[PDB]
Image 1 (cartoon, rainbow, N blue to C red):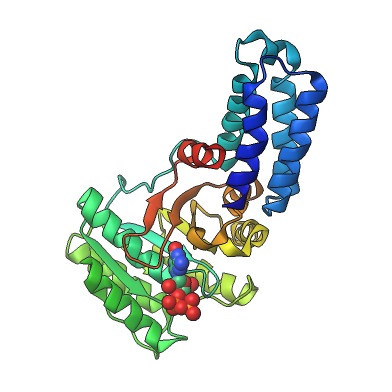
Image 2: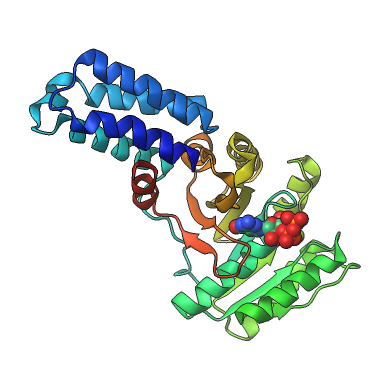
Length: 294
Ligand SMILES: Nc1nc2c(ncn2[C@@H]2O[C@H](COP(=O)(O)OP(=O)(O)O)[C@@H](OP(=O)(O)OP(=O)(O)O)[C@H]2O)c(=O)[nH]1
Ligand SMILES: [Mg+2]
């Protein structure tokens, strides 16, 4: 990423210094603010991050250590993690089976792909008997896409077709999920390229009839700051439990990851890091912060 190089260079010079002047701390923070802003991180997030470092990096606290540069570096890390999220947020599949995970996103965010990815993760790493279904009757080849995905990853597919109504489709799928003791039902959805009441009304009807335990917004990382604004929109119309940030491999900037948790107020739970089925990665903020700073 270009954020990783910029921050790592700015921090590296400070680490060696055995004492940091207040001007030295202020100058380094201005360079950090520019790097995050250049990475499409939202100003509300950058502003709060810089203020939190400044308060904790007062020279008295930083200069007390024998490695003041090191102490400053590791404040920046701690506050980056705080912005990206709280520890690891997982899906609650511990409630009454079947566990319904309803997935939303605008078209091309990668929700259908992510449906597959998640089903492989739940069966392989959690030994969950999984069933998936598609309420995207607007594109026919889409339903097939899920079907093909479901066999590559080894979950079960509940069939649907163009003529039928999304509410009827998920009601059938839950009924069936109960009858064969499935652990989770993942429910794919249609996307409209914009968060419009047309899209929200359909999701909220599905959502209402099927009481999902997790509502996951799939958002595309290479839309940068829009990802947070798009998810803040869906969240305002129908509350989210988690976000899946897809196409992280190609962004090369970041910012959606730093921005989503604080703009939306809900966590990034998963992270799409490849076109392949294996490329789903639970979101651990500590690991991401470490990579950004080296
Ligand atoms: N690099 C990368 N790509 C991802 C990731 N997740 C999804 N994609 C890509 O997103 C594209 C759209 O996926 P869909 O699953 O159809 O998205 P949708 O359900 O929201 O409509 C796919 O591209 P496609 O159909 O192969 O081509 P195109 O649609 O991009 O033209 C897929 O390969 C990811 O984590 N990393
Ligand atoms: Mg689709």
